[PDB]
Image: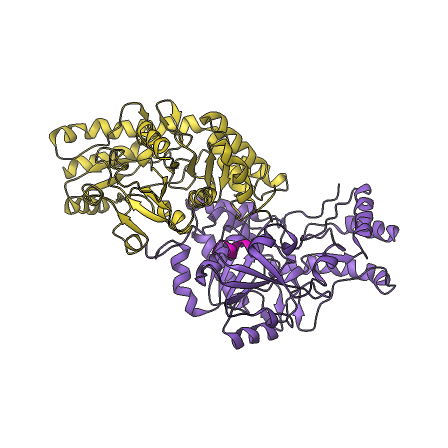
Chain colours: A purple, B yellow
């Protein structure tokens, strides 16, 4: 069967992992760890980058870094991963959900200010599908109300917004290194980006409980074995990105006649935003047309899957959070979004099979 | 070298297997296998692997629904994560002095610190040596307290037949390179012995339904699991070899211990260790630092252990020491950990002993 995703295989991961084993150091904060850190810092322009076991932990570290007390309201979309909210709820924060914009499925930068209260301190924007949000409106809103901006660029690796890299535009940035991402770091991984220099000294403390105790913290240490796996794929960062971009536009150029026919809808990439081709989604009227395609693709041995059940609709989202405004584009558009098979090791032969099955359905 | 990460020689073979499967993320193939291995071998109801023991400790505090104000009893002579994991839930830490023979929490000094706010007592198995669990379990049962086992060093070691980590409601394993089983450098394991705590355990490890409830990503990569699975395969071989090297230390350092010059580790009846470390107790902080500096001159790396948390600026802020600090501070400043690991050649072990006896 043709899966929806397969972990990035450069073919050099095995060689770099033997260097970590040969060095005799496999624990966190080792050699290849700091090398991946130096890589991300200079390439993206961030002041400091620390590697975590997961993007979830990075988000948890951020909520711990900004010193969140129970009662603090954090604004975020409900069309995101559960880790985005749970990381802040753990600190006692209440979540204020805001509807998304139907073109990019990102948080509407115009509806944010209405959700701001005296209890609000943090706003965490999610760069869905690698497509950056309107940062030149959000950062101004933060500046206007003295708020912190934590970027959830879990899918925004090798993505930029008007030049600047994602995870860099904001006080804190969070990268993901799961096997379902552009760079897998051995299956599990994450990265905390500390762009604000005034948050660095404490970030080092909470990274290793107390000054590597002085204060609370955790063990946000990713093994050096995983580091070597990541460093191997950062070496082919431009090769991986360009290949995924090639496979991405192949989907777009073949589904464009259907989009211009009004049958389906294609992803929108705003001016100034450069994606990384993390995923390719389409829109199918309702939830019955999407399922009809899902079952159709499954019959052709092709794996397709939707994305993100709205957090505000979940029973735990009704307890720790609240959807401000009108649920206009969040729930509806989520039930029609379908993700197509897209990964680095995807052969062009199989992609033609997927596309042929799509056009066959329509 | 004080410690070198355990190398069986078959780690590479099992990692290629994980890579060939096209799945390296958490809860993968080798993840289940490691969890199945630990459950049968030790007798645990449910074992879940974590990125670290610290994560497991935090997962434990989140599992028992620790609210701000709740008191947690533990020795101050423990790793920072043992206390830091509970403070994250807003708990207050109540430190209890140790017993000088095993450096474990004194089972007789615990009950004097129990209040109405006390909810969890977390014992720490030092050097793989078990705490007096029969007394501790009877304590908790009487005062309705949870027992979270911090067996970060007690893996493969037992207490009166029962493996450490399975004696109490929640246990915690560590898989660091400085431990007996490294799991690719980082790794941990939460042991859910209480069956009534199993259902909520799997939820908080994967946020919800596998949202539904608070939780985190306590998932460890299948790459590390593949590394760990190779280590658990040769569990007996590693254990016995480390136990062999441990006996060589005790046999040679016994005359000094009987002379009164130093003090060797004490192992209570019914307690079987796993030889995580061989500590000698000098006379003071000056005698220890003198040996450390002497061994360093002979290019031999020795090291002490963590400083009592109740003296640290965070411990006096987030916790309180109950009773008189009679042994914790003093014994900590005279304890010295000798070089000990699985790949320690017989040639280099004698060299250390030759340097030790030469100092005395």
Main SS class of the magenta portion in the image: helix
Q: Quadrant of the C terminus of chain B?
A: top left
Nearer-the-camera pick, A117 or B214 = A117
Q: Residue at x 70, y 70 (%)?
A: A270
The reply to whether residue B128 is visible in this rendering is yes
Q: Is residue B330 above or below residue B250?
A: below
Q: Residue furthest left?
A: B259
- Indicate the position of residue A271 as horizontal and vertical percent values: 69, 73
Q: Is residue A105 left or right of residue A207?
A: right
- Indicate the position of residue A167 as horizontal and vertical percent values: 55, 64
Q: Is residue A87 magenta?
A: yes
Q: Quadrant of residue A336?
A: bottom right
User: Which residues, given as a range, are shown in magenta?
Assistant: A86-91
Nearer-the-camera pick, A92 or A63 = A92
Q: Residue at x 81, y 57 (%)?
A: A285
- Indicate the position of residue B29 as horizontal and vertical percent values: 59, 36
Q: Is residue B77 magenta?
A: no
Q: Is residue A155 above or below residue B281?
A: below
Nearer-the-camera pick, A277 or A108 = A108
Q: Quadrant of the N terminus of chain B?
A: top left
Q: Residue furthest front?
A: B116
Total residue callouts: 0
Q: Is residue B114 left or right of residue B286?
A: right
Nearer-the-camera pick, B32 or A15 = B32
Q: Is residue B125 left or right of residue A227?
A: left
The reply to whether residue A247 is visible in this rendering is no
Q: Quadrant of residue A152?
A: bottom right
- Indicate the position of residue B260 as horizontal and vertical percent values: 12, 32
Q: Is residue B313 left or right of residue B240?
A: left
């Amino acid at each position: 069967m043709i899966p929806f995703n397969a972990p990035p295989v450069v073919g050099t991961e095995l060689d770099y992992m033997q260097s970590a084993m040969g060095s005799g150091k496999l624990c966190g904060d080792g050699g290849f760890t700091r090398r991946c850190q130096q890589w991300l810092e200079q390439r993206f322009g961030s002041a400091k980058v620390l590697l975590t076991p997961s993007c979830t932990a990075s988000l948890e570290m951020a909520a711990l870094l900004l010193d969140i007390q129970p009662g603090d309201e954090v604004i975020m979309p409900s069309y995101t991963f559960v880790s985005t909210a749970n990381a802040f709820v753990l600190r006692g924060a209440k979540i204020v959900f805001v509807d998304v914009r139907p073109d990019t499925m990102n948080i509407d930068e115009t509806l944010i200010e209405a959700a701001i209260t005296d209890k609000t301190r943090v706003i965490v924007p999610v760069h869905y599908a690698g497509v950056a949000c309107e940062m030149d409106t959000i950062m101004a809103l933060a500046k206007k109300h003295n708020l912190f901006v934590v970027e959830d660029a879990a899918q925004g690796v090798m993505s930029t917004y008007k030049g600047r890299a994602l995870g860099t535009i904001g006080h804190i940035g969070c990268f993901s290194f799961h096997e379902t991402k552009n760079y897998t770091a051995g299956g599990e991984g994450g990265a905390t980006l500390i762009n604000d220099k005034a948050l660095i000294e404490r970030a080092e403390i909470i990274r290793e409980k107390g000054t590597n105790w002085r204060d609370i913290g955790s063990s946000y240490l990713m093994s050096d074995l995983q580091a070597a796996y990541l460093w191997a794929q950062l070496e082919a960062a431009d090769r991986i990105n360009q290949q995924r971009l090639a496979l991405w536009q192949n989907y777009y150029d073949a589904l464009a006649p259907l989009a211009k026919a009004g049958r389906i809808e294609l992803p929108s990439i705003p001016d100034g935003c450069v994606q990384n081709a993390h995923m390719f989604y389409i829109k199918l009227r309702d939830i019955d047309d999407r399922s009809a395609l899902i079952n159709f693709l499954k019959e052709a041995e092709i794996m397709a899957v939707f994305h993100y059940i709205p957090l505000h609709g979940c029973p735990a989202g009704e307890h720790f959070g609240e959807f401000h405004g009108e649920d206009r584009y969040t729930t509806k558009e989520s039930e029609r979004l379908l993700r197509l098979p897209l990964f680095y090791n995807l052969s062009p032969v199989n992609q033609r099979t997927v596309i042929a099955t799509l056009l066959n359905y329509f």
